[PDB]
Image (cartoon, grey):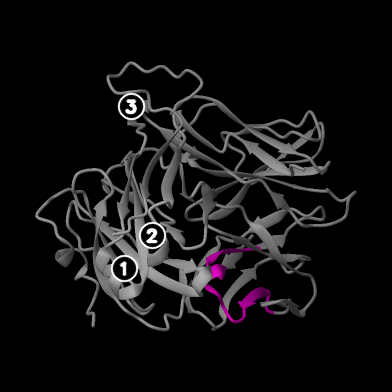
Amino acid sequence: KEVEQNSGPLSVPEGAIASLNCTYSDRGSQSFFWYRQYSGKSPELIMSIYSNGDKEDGRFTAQLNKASQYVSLLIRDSQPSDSATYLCAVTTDSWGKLQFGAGTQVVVTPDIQNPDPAVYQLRDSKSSDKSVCLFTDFDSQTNVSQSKDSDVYITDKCVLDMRSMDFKSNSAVAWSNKSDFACANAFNNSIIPE
Amino acid sequence: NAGVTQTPKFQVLKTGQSMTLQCAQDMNHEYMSWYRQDPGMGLRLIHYSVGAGITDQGEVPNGYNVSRSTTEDFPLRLLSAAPSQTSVYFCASRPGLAGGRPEQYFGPGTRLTVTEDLKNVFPPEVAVFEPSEAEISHTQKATLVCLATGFYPDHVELSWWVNGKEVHSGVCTDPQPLKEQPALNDSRYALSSRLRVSATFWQDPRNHFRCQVQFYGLSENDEWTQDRAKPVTQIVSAEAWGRAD
């Protein structure tokens, strides 16, 4: 038996529709489900569908097409707080045995209203001149490159959300143990700035 | 008031050790399942149980035993740990067709890392880096970074605390750790986090900021014949005060 989802990670601009689909091989299947799993958390049931057509819940729409044997999930007016992995599941028993798809990571990237891309040097609070660099405030179209050096470390971008100001920002962190290393070098590899 | 609970949340095992994953279910649900989830294949059923006294095999039963002597408890047992049993295990339950609904409720998961050699275990070093004064003056905001480095296995929980209270707004933590040595199998890990506050909040010197990393390591009297301190389950933290600048 086959339950098969789209492969990810899928990048979606804030405000657009994130979409996943799932095809299933067993034409008898009665019940279809979408579970959402935040990173390091458990799968949480978000949509159930049993009959052909559309079902709706807030910003979620599920569609079941029994003739073509797929279930979809549409996430309308996508929010960065929707960034998670979404898992198709299909019932395979007359008890309710569940078979899961492999899941698809959705990344909803924030709409950065006032881009101010900059790189900053941060100092250790106590530890005698230890060095970390922060790339922050760039737009969501911006790619961050691993400047492939042995001991220069660079994280993927991550999105923080200051609720008290309705302000999101992208950032990426780089560091190295004192190997001819300054913040000028750290990021440049991230393909073509402004 | 509990729901589905799993104990322990995290475990290291040396290859060949046995272990038992506890699963407890408050809600009197008839049906319980155990799944593994691996960073490639989604959730795979291992064993399931329709009722007390009854267990049956899922699609990957091999290397695992299960028991259901009571309705509340469905422990999962690994007779002899193999590295490929490194995974996250989820226990799930549902009323079970006498109680009607098909919704499966999931426990919070148990992360398991199987290693060749327990000499591989290392707690994190943890440091906080104070905001740039350039960021402060161009943006009127202030980002602190937390760095946790050199830990194995990658069983940590990093939290940010301001004036004694855990915060979530203004925070992101890498979803994935960096491997310090990518081509190495029991490589140690690095994690970063950021907390961003207004410049004005960071410039108040009575404001306290603490990055806290709970590491899960060696515990219930594992043997330790080495020079360095036993890498036990512990919290490692770093902190800073606001700065009028």
Q: Which mark is residue B177?
A: none
Tag 3 subunit = B
- Residue drawn at x 79%, y 57% as measured from the top left: B102
Mark 2 crowdedness (10 Å alpha carbons): few <14, some 14-19, many ≥20 = many
| Residue under label 2 | B202
Q: Residue A158, can we see it?
A: no
Amino acid at the residue labelled 2? Trp
Gap in Å between the C-alphas at discs 3 and 1?
Answer: 44 Å
| Residue under label 1 | B136
Q: Earlier in the sequence, mark 2 or mark 3?
A: 3
Q: Earlier in the sequence, mark 2 or mark 1?
A: 1
Q: Are marks 3 and 1 in contact (CB under 8 Å)?
A: no
Mark 3 crowdedness (10 Å alpha carbons): few <14, some 14-19, many ≥20 = some
| Residue under label 3 | B119
Query: Along the horizontal axis of the image, is A115 left or right of B73?
Result: left
Tag nearer the camera, 3 or 1: 1
Q: Are marks 2 and 1 in contact (CB under 8 Å)?
A: yes
Q: Position of residue A105 (x, y in %)?
A: 50, 65
Looking at the rendered structure, the secondary structure element under dot 2 is: helix
Looking at the rendered structure, the secondary structure element under dot 3 is: helix
Tag 2 subunit = B
